[PDB]
Amino acid sequence: KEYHIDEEVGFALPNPQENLPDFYNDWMFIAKHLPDLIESGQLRERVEKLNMLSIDHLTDHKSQRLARLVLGCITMAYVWGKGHGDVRKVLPRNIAVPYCQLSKKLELPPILVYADCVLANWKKKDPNKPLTYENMDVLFSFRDGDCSKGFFLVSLLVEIAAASAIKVIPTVFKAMQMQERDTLLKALLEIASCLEKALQVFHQIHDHVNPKAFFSVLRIYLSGWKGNPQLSDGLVYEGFWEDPKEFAGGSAGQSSVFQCFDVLLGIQQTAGGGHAAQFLQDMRRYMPPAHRNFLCSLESNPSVREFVLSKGDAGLREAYDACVKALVSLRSYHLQIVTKYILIPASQQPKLEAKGTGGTDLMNFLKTVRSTTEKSLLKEG
Ligand code: HEM
Ligand SMILES: N[C@@H](Cc1c[nH]c2ccccc12)C(=O)O
Ligand SMILES: OCCc1c[nH]c2ccccc12
Ligand SMILES: [C-]#N
């Protein structure tokens, strides 16, 4: 079965739509000139003075996902505004109704998710040149000097690097079924190599994303309205819903690729009934329908951990541990990123636990997730 996985990019949208049809030019002009409109402070006036447009004219899947990115970026720009404190609790019917109808059609929440701002928000400058940062550029930004290009593309490049292991997954379960030791050993080491390579692509974040520019500018526009003191009851969608509704902000916890390795290796991140387990499970509803199907498809298969444990095979245990060590390394490095990009900039701000964009007590959350990964290390059985 097909889960919209590409051979070249993985779970990213393969060469996404760059521009909407002529009927939706009113939405496109607002989203493209978004840094200018916020800085002037005239964004909120133009969204209110807009016409309610029907979503029927959107032809294909690539167009529909771009429209989610267009309307999603505008919604975040309308709510947070300049990003200082003054917020809009109400989203006008002219934008709220078409966005909710598109969200329901694509089985996604009416909020900017990872699939919009990362997986669909990219273009390559030269089509003949291979996929690299210097050849790539984002489609939409929130502000000037907010490091949108560096942040969204590095996240995408790590996604693509790790997605090289997705093609190895069919080999893993076939080797278990056919009872093929040498094949499974080579397959697991290949996955471990991909995750080690993804860590090297991660290093690029320091070059292209500024710590102060991320925290005080860009981070506010990725934040949502679930477990948020600024929008306590949430957001009222005028015309569509009767009561204010809570929805979580964007995170890479909404990525299928990164959740899939925990599932493949039998790292029970979603089990336990804890706050960390609850978040990662809830974020699957913030993923595309096809990507959600892939995750439980992996859960439906025999456990790789249980297979390797029963064998009494030092080489097969080592190859399995190589994957787990690679995931620990990525999560240890991610926490170092958190120190540089959240923790240190937060202490520099002028006049109790810190919360992420997704809506978690981040330091306790991320360490629990890493601890669960560390516990999965076999260490000679
Ligand atoms: C600007 C740099 C980054 C910061 C400050 C950051 C911070 C965080 C925070 C606070 C969370 C907790 C969830 C939430 O409340 O939002 C989180 C989760 C996560 N981040 Fe990041 N992150 C960054 C970049 C990345 C990148 C580039 C990746 C990989 C492409 C990544 C992968 C993840 C994953 C997979 C999770 C879910 C928890 C887990 O499985 O470990 N992050 N991040
Ligand atoms: N969760 C991060 C922001 C973030 C990192 N990667 C993302 C991908 C998509 C949306 C948001 C993000 C924070 O709280 O600072
Ligand atoms: O939180 C660290 C980022 C991360 C978790 N799982 C992954 C799999 C591949 C690449 C990065 C990650
Ligand atoms: C990273 N969220």
Image (tube, helix red, strand yellow):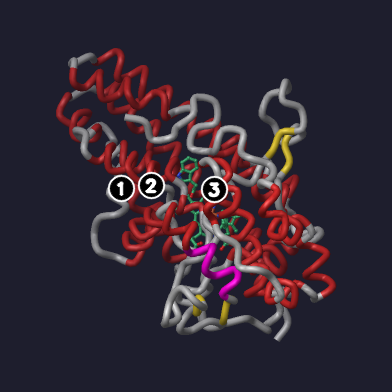
Mark 1: give few (<14), some (14-19) or many (20+) Cα within 10 Å.
Answer: few
Mark 3 vs 2, N-terminal side: 3
Disc 3, disc 2: CB below 8 Å? no
Above or below, 136 against 284 in this view is above
Residue 352 relative to residue 296: left or right: right
The image quadrant that residue 135 belongs to is top right
| Label 3 C-beta lies within 8 Å of the nearest ligand 2 atom | no
Residue placed furthest toward the bottom:
351
Q: CA distance from mark 1 to mark 2?
A: 31 Å
Q: CA distance from mark 3 to mark 2?
A: 14 Å
* Extent of the magenta region: 93-100
Residue 343 visible? The answer is no
Q: Residue at x 25, y 18 (%)?
A: 175
Q: Residue at x 57, y 82 (%)?
A: 89
Mark 3 vs 1, N-terminal side: 3
Q: Element under label 1?
A: helix
Q: Residue at x 44, y 43 (%)?
A: 258
Above or below, 157 against 80 in this view is above
The image quadrant that residue 189 belongs to is top left
Residue placed furthest toward the left:
310
Q: Magenta-highlighted stretch: main secondary structure?
A: helix
Residue annotated with mark 3 = 64
Q: Residue 379's spot in the image, x, y percent?
A: 29, 36
**What amino acid is at disc 1?**
Lys
Residue annotated with mark 1 = 375
Disc 1, disc 2: CB below 8 Å? no
Label placed on residue 289: 2
**What amino acid is at disc 3?**
Gln
Q: Residue 261's spot in the image, x, y percent?
A: 38, 39
Q: Residue 329's spot in the image, x, y percent?
A: 49, 42
